[PDB]
Image (cartoon, coloured by chain):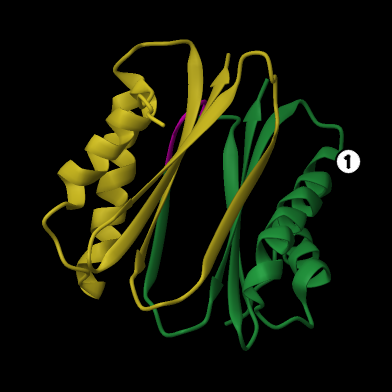
Chain colours: A green, B yellow
Amino acid sequence: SQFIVDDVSKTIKEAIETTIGGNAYQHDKVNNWTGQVVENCLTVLTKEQKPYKYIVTAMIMQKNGAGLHTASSCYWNNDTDGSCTVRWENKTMYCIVSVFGLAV
Amino acid sequence: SQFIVDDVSKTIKEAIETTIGGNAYQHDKVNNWTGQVVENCLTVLTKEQKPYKYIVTAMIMQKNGAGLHTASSCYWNNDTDGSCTVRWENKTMYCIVSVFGLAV
């Protein structure tokens, strides 16, 4: 098997790695990191100047063996609106970002 | 001090408690529960027949002592669009739901 990664996923993952890669979970710093991830991934989207509203959410979980499950549902225009979720991890943390684009 | 809980937060929290209250984290069942929470909270919003697109996200984390941080950022119309986040927990799990409404 083989695969080529779509552009949105690749550029979101890069924004995460740039923002937090090389770092170990530190409770007092992570709220600022999580805010930086969302802001840098929103900038990934808005620099393209496309006619959409965007929502970007991110979560950073310390790695400790806990189970975690996420899901989303939307009421929108399925012909034009969409979302992408990316998961990223290192030895001490998992970071999941989801972006949603809604045509205006 | 005192407070009165806004209607959206109260009705989202009730949808979570109805969906998962009384239950203990069980790995194989939680993906379905998380999907049920999002669907029941989206129904909370869409039954009001208002002129908005909605995004509902939910996360269920097993309680194990792990740190967790979440954040969101949006590019939208600040005069009309908005969001609410609710956190809920019992002895074995935390469930966080965020809803975002974007005027059409």
Q: Classify residue B74 as left or right of residue A15.
A: left
Residue lying at 40% horizontally and 51% vertically, measured from the top left: B96
Q: Quadrant of the C terminus of chain B?
A: top right
Q: Is residue A14 visible?
A: yes
Residue B98 to residue A13: above or below: above
Q: Residues within 10 Å of mark 1 (few under 14, many from 20)?
A: few
Q: Classify residue A5 as left or right of residue B5.
A: right
Going by the numbered disc 1, the residue's amino acid type is Lys
Q: Classify residue B78 as left or right of residue B63.
A: right
Query: Residue A21: x and y, percent?
Result: 77, 77
Residue A7 position by quadrant: bottom right
Query: Residue B40: x and y, percent?
Result: 26, 37
Q: Classify residue A94 as left or right of residue A26.
A: left
SS class, disc 1: loop
Residue B31 position by quadrant: bottom left
Residue lying at 60% horizontally and 21% vertically, measured from the top left: B81
Which residue position holds label 1? A47
Q: Which residues are magenta?
A: A73-77
Total number of numbered labels? 1
Residue lying at 76% horizontally and 52% vertically, measured from the top left: A41
Residue closest to the eye, B41 or A26: A26
